[PDB]
Structure formats: structure tokens, C-alpha cells
Amino acid sequence: VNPTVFFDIAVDGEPLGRVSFELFADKVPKTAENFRALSTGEKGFGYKGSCFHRIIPGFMCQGGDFTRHNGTGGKSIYGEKFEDENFILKHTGPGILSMANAGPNTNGSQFFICTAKTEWLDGKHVVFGKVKEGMNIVEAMERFGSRNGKTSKKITIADCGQL
């Protein structure tokens, strides 16, 4: 019953592979629904064609800024921003999907996929999903990051949607 969404990832336009996520709609329904709808594009905007702008190996891959492509944009399906729904789930290790923010109650569209345990984020970022298939593809993406987060090649969501 929890939804599954996919991203098809490309590297300088060349297909890399597919990542699928389970969204924890049973625990964070509002947050899960935002990501789901942005991944299908059903509200007329969303993730398709957007990039992963910041990738720090051994930490995380951050994306979802589909309006400015650099970490300073994005919007939710509820408006520019929405509240921190709850902090029931924790950042327990690689594969966790979590909301980026700029302060309390400032969730938009930006998210990150953790490639390490990031326990210091517990209670500050809302965890709402986890990689189900294709963690190997996230690992391959990570190799195009750097210490300061700039990517060596352009990493994009070529297609996405719901499975």
C-alpha cells in the first residue's frame, strides 16, 4: 500500500540506471504525497528533467530544485513551503530519503538520499522514504560528486513516475 516511485538517472544525457523508492505514506502521509506527486508530475510541475546539484561522497546526494537547479529553488504541491510533519523516522544509514530545508517548517521540493548514517540530522529533517531498488545506481552517482558537492558531470532525472 505504500507507494513506490522511480527515477531514471542520466549522466551527461547518457542513461545510468533506475532507482526506486518506497515512500512511507503510513507514517508521513503529507510529506510522502508531495514527493509522489512531484515524481508523477500530475500537478503540472515536478522532478522530471531536474538535476542533482550537490553530491558529497560518503554523505548524501541532494536534488529536487526544479526551478533554479542549484539549491536555491523548488516548491511543494502545498505552496512554497510546508511544515515538518513529524520526526518519527530516523536517519539510520545509506538509502534513507529525507527532506532538505532552511529552518523549521520550510520543506519545499528539495530532498536528499543519504549514502551514510547521518544521525545528527535526526529531529531536524523529515525522513519519508528509502531506496528499494537500485542502491547500486546511487553508489554510481556518488562517484560523480566531490568534497564541496560540485558534480563533475551533469546528473539528471531523465524520467520518473510511480510504479
Image (cartoon, rainbow, N blue to C red):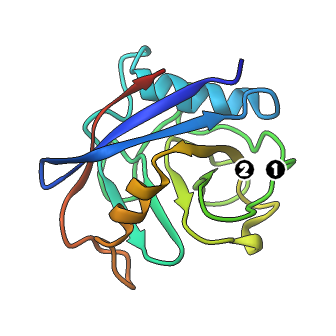
Frontmost residue, 136 versus 65: 136
Asked if 41 appears above or below 152 in the picture, the reply is above
- Residue type at mark 2 is Val
Query: What residue did someone put label 1 on?
Result: 89
Looking at the image, residue 128 sits to the left or right of residue 79; the answer is right
Q: Circle 2 sits in a helix, a strand or a loop, which is it?
A: loop
Which residue lies at the image location 72% right of the left edge and 50% below the top edge? Answer: 126
Which residue lies at the image location 53% right of the left edge and 33% below the top edge? Answer: 76
Which residue lies at the image location 49% right of the left edge and 48% below the top edge? Answer: 110
Frontmost residue, 142 versus 54: 142
Residue 78 in view (yes/no): no
Pointers 1 and 2 in contact (C-beta within 8 Å): yes
Looking at the image, residue 75 sits to the left or right of residue 18; the answer is right
Quadrant in which residue 153 is drawn: bottom left
Frontmost residue, 1 versus 72: 1
Tell me how far mark 1 sits from mark 2, CA to CA: 7 Å
